[PDB]
Image 1 (tube, rainbow over the protein chains, first blue to last red):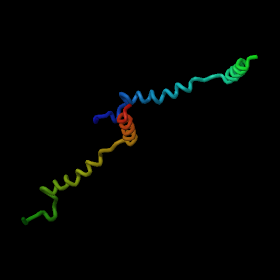
Image 2: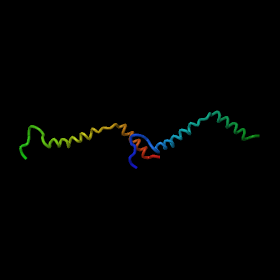
Image 3: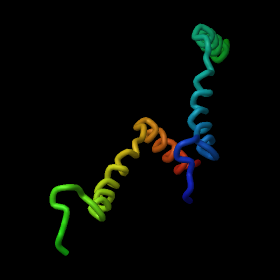
Image 4: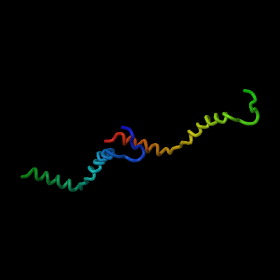
Length: 51
Length: 51
């Protein structure tokens, strides 16, 4: 339709699209310690071989 | 007709024609801030897409 808010603010569902392109920001806060990744890879190999 | 004011002054409707060619001067006082035009274009595009 017509009669849009050309000057004031983003409103309605244009905020939702921000969620859809802010979720990528939440997906990169999931930090991890590298040395824990190497530790767990090592213990995984050892437990997978077995005897 | 005859008997016009060849030396003294513009008079009668020759002032009106000045209005007709001064209105163009009123039409160029309508100044705007450019960064507000860009702001409003931006918020218009964002509100037009929507979700």
